Amino acid sequence: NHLHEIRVFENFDMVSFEKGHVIVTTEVVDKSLNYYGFAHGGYIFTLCDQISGLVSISTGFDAVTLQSSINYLKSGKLGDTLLIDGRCVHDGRTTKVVDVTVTNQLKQEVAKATFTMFVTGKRK
Amino acid sequence: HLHEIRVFENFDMVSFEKGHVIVTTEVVDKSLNYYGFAHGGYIFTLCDQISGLVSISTGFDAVTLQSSINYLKSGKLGDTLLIDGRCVHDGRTTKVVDVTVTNQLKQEVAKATFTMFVTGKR
Ligand SMILES: CC(C)(COP(=O)(O)OP(=O)(O)OC[C@H]1O[C@@H](n2cnc3c(N)ncnc32)[C@H](O)[C@@H]1OP(=O)(O)O)[C@@H](O)C(=O)NCCC(=O)NCCS
Ligand SMILES: CC(C)(COP(=O)(O)OP(=O)(O)OC[C@H]1O[C@@H](n2cnc3c(N)ncnc32)[C@H](O)[C@@H]1OP(=O)(O)O)[C@@H](O)C(=O)NCCC(=O)NCCS
Ligand SMILES: [Cl-]
Ligand SMILES: [Cl-]
Ligand SMILES: [Cl-]
């Protein structure tokens, strides 16, 4: 299942959920377009932040985002399908670090991010 | 200077000058995650929007190329956020914007740096 793990601010469909590795997909719709015709930076960032929270949960912990760095490599356009992949690269006592990639249907990398998460407790 | 950008998270304009834009907003429930905090993407979007405004204030259209953000203190229901964006580098091809988010108690809530890639004259 894994619906209801987090509050959904930007819609996505769950693809796979495993320890330290979560994959979801979404489609770029009108709501996310800026006036330049691109998926806005905050939309792409939120998809990555959401998945970083899911990845922390997948390691067995609640955590808050402490710091994040994101690169926008290629624009997302109306109708694009985005595959968002989050992988834990450091599963620490106090911090988790998550690498996130966002890829389109042409397998071009749209964005990449690193999230540093501060652990607040053991899950459920 | 409303009208400059598409608004994804609401804000009220406080001041708009060349290289320096300030806006304000209130944290409402729709932005709260299950931990009761304004979610990271909501804060980031406020910062990304003001970085767009700052780039426009310098005379240029730009797209976000890279951004780093630190979440220093959580935003809570009812908090008033002051978002201040300052161009620290007004370059030919890139603009760099230093963004600070503070609360009513004057505590620093978040700090971000946006690297904007210039696409043309506004
Ligand atoms: C920053 C850092 C300490 C975060 O720790 P973490 O995410 O909890 O990761 P770990 O679980 O692997 O713990 C690393 C060490 O920090 C300690 N630590 C973790 N959380 C701690 C906390 N809350 N308070 C005190 N120590 C803590 C652990 O006990 C562990 O100590 P050990 O070496 O005796 O086993 C860790 O990522 C790190 O050591 N990074 C390298 C920092 C570095 O070398 N910087 C450049 C040179 S200064
Ligand atoms: C990265 C950087 C080049 C971006 O350029 P910018 O935002 O356009 O900034 P500026 O307008 O001040 O231009 C800086 C230089 O880059 C050149 N430049 C700007 N845009 C360019 C472009 N599109 N293509 C080729 N050159 C360009 C300018 O001509 C200027 O060179 P000049 O000293 O001969 O006049 C600039 O911020 C910089 O020089 N940063 C320092 C990089 C550094 O020292 N890194 C560590 C050591 S390698
Ligand atoms: Cl690419
Ligand atoms: Cl826009
Ligand atoms: Cl406040």
Image (spheres, coloured by chain):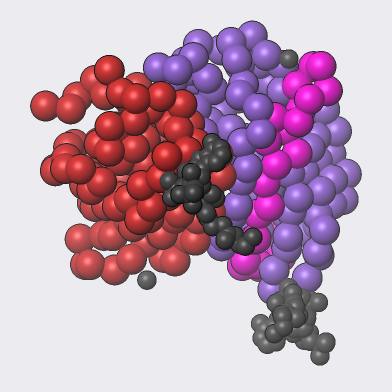
Chain colours: A red, B purple
Horizontal side, residue A46 vs residue B53: left or right: left
Residue B56 visible (yes or no):
no
User: Residue B70 falls in which quadrant of the image?
Assistant: top right
Measured as percent of width and height from the top left, residue A33 is found at 43, 44
Horizontal side, residue B66 vs residue A15: left or right: right
Residues shaded magenta = B100-122
Horizontal side, residue A18 vs residue A11: left or right: left
* In the foreground, B12 or A60: A60
Queried whether the magenta region covers residue B104, the answer comes back as yes
Majority secondary structure in the magenta region: strand
Instruction: Please name the residue shown 62% across and 66% down the image.
Output: B117
Query: Vertically, is A107 above or below B20?
Result: below
Instruction: Please name the residue shown 81% across and 54% down the image.
Output: B87
Horizontal side, residue B12 vs residue B105: left or right: left
Measured as percent of width and height from the top left, residue B30 is found at 47, 15
Instruction: Please name the residue shown 35% across and 56% down the image.
Output: A89
